Image (spheres, coloured by chain):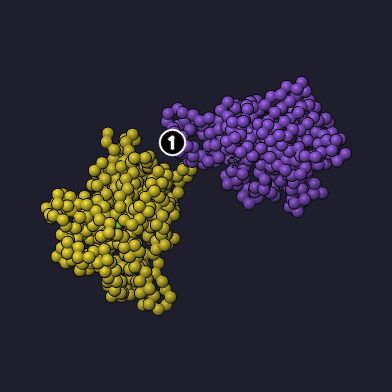
Chain colours: A yellow, B purple
Amino acid sequence: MNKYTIAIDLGYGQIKGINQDNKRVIFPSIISSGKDRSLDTFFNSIDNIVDNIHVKILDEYFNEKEYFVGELAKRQPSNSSFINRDNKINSEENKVLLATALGLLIPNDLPNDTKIHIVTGLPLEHFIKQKQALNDMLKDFEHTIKFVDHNFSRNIKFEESNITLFPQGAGAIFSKINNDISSLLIKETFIGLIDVGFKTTDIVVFRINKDKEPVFEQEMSATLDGLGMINIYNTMDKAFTDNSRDGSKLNTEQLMLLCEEGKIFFKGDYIDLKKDLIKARKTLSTNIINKADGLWGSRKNSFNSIMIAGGGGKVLYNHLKLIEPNMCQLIDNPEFANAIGYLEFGKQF
Amino acid sequence: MNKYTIAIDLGYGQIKGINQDNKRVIFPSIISSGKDRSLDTFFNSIDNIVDNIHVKILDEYFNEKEYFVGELAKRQPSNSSFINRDNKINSEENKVLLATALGLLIPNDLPNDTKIHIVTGLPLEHFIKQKQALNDMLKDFEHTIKFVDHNFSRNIKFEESNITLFPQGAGAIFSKINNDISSLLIKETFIGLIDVGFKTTDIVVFRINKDKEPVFEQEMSATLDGLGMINIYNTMDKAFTDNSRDGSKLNTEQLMLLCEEGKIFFKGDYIDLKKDLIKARKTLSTNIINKADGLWGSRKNSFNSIMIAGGGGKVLYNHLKLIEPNMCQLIDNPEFANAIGYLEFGKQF
Ligand SMILES: Nc1ncnc2c1ncn2[C@@H]1O[C@H](COP(=O)(O)OP(=O)(O)O)[C@@H](O)[C@H]1O
Ligand SMILES: Nc1ncnc2c1ncn2[C@@H]1O[C@H](COP(=O)(O)OP(=O)(O)O)[C@@H](O)[C@H]1O
Ligand SMILES: [Mg+2]
Ligand SMILES: [Mg+2]
């Protein structure tokens, strides 16, 4: 039989993955040590595993470790702080996320002889830099995952010539739109994906040729490293302590709940910080537009379709529209632009 | 008669020896024939005599037989078999290996009448069984050594009152910690010494009395024959045929090369067995602690300090930590633990 295919993303906000059979999972990039759950099972019936990932993972010692990951880790008081999370792609923090991303996206009772084309991702300026670090991790990733309170296990191990690395935004606009953007690309134009992520924002362009095929440019395209949603959480963390004036600083959930809405429910009251949320987004909108003119001279006028991506692009699509209005548009899945872009451009082999 | 002192060992993995002047040598217990080293002499400087032991050996019938021994014999393909080596202490192998480190540690400018006190060792359980045979052999010893490529020779012959017979691990914590553990030993405790050698594993304890004197317990102390580093080399060798997936097999030099590192360079590329190296070393460490507690019931609670000896325990110390944490510890010279213990406790005469 043919080899299976899974395209995941190790993005800093949330793991965004999809398989060969077009089933997708999404959960935030927070881990926590798992503790025994049969009690909270009894109060509320679990119909979603994604909310409730209690899970055991074997290792090279074949020693299991309980984990809370995803939505269940965010409610825990003892989880990862998630603002000082490592960029080391071979870390166990990245392993458990990658274990669950490969754990959910495998259906039951597959033949054990076949292997899976896994397709991961890297930052654009850190693709070459962190190429062999994930190559070492995926060669080292020999683990057996066991979902507690769902009771289905996967033996996840990969040899050589099965992993496939791509940069972020590589196949999201090269592929994934090529069947639909081919009528829009005409002659010597630039398409551009702008993925607004957690830690970084990512700019990738593709010149199409005379023969209507896109080709890459790296001096018009880079990673806005350290510029992204991370500037919004850190600013709005100070915005609460400026508005509380008590020394009360938000925890992991309260800050993440804040920048989605702007009204944290503090002491039986919503503390209004909608205006400072606009200001932190506008400074992020400042630091992507002015950096775009650093990468683009008059070639911003040489665009036919700007696309913006990322979950951070969802709340900023009309706000980051001021790059080139009436030409920029939204990618059809704002979160899953990279993953399906990894899927279609991973099936080219 | 200011008689000299040299303390040696008969370790199967390698020979460990030291003189009165604390000059110490270490070399593997591998022999081969001696062939004329004049061609390589002009190429590379034969400088380290311990690395390059081409040695001329006479007997009582003046039968000169050159031998490559040690590191150079390990480089030879036609070397001693050494993984199924005969355990006869009166072997010609042991005739060479004992006479090897003598002239390598017999100093210059000795008086005419002055002899040398030699201190040797036996396995602890076989110290009753094999006391006669080494005493047969040391009385037998009447030879003459000569060093090719370094241009000096020694006379070598001994009688009784020059011989000294203490078992393996006997004087290592009797002396060598004697005035140092005296502040640690207080009242009615045991001290732990475990020799993790190549072929054999020794366990030896000492009850200290009310009078701060160590006394020996033969029933809490035994030689674990068949347990040691020789299991790990033999385990990973079949594992090398596994991960190569071709039935190809190492040589004797690659055998000792492997489980010092675990990443053997084979057919233009590394072959990775690092997982199984962690597996087998933890597996042997499991087998030590259980057989340690085979002799140790609740008398493990009557310990105050455990030391480990042998070359294996130095690289097992993280996994041999699980006997009693922060009470178990590593001796400073894991190889020369028996040697200095043979030295000072051999200096009774
Ligand atoms: N509905 C929403 N409201 C507010 N912010 C959102 C929403 N959806 C996503 N986000 C933001 O987008 C980020 C997700 O970015 P993502 O596309 O996963 O990039 P990365 O690949 O860097 O993780 C989150 O950290 C979150 O702050
Ligand atoms: N640096 C090292 N790395 C791996 N193994 C080692 C190292 N040093 C010593 N050893 C192991 O320890 C053994 C030496 O044990 P040793 O103390 O000489 O006991 P014996 O008296 O039985 O020969 C060797 O066979 C070797 O496998
Ligand atoms: Mg992203
Ligand atoms: Mg020994």
Q: Position of residue B90 (x, y in %)?
A: 72, 25
Up-down: is A49 above or below A304?
A: above
* Residue A344 seen anywhere in this rendered image of the structure: yes
Front one among B345 and A154: B345
At a point 30% along the width and 50% down the height, the residue shown is A166
Q: Position of residue A6 (x, y in %)?
A: 29, 45
Three-letter amino acid code at the position of disc 1: Gly
Q: Position of residue A219 (x, y in %)?
A: 27, 59
- Left or right, residue B329 beside residue A306: right
Q: Which residue is mark 1?
A: B268
> Hey, which residue is sitting farthest bottom in the picture?
A245
Up-down: is A74 above or below B203?
A: below
Quadrant of the image for the N terminus of chain B?
top right
Q: Position of residue B39 (x, y in %)?
A: 59, 31
Q: Which quarter of the picture shows residue B232?
A: top right
* Residue B205 seen anywhere in this rendered image of the structure: no
Q: How many marks?
A: 1
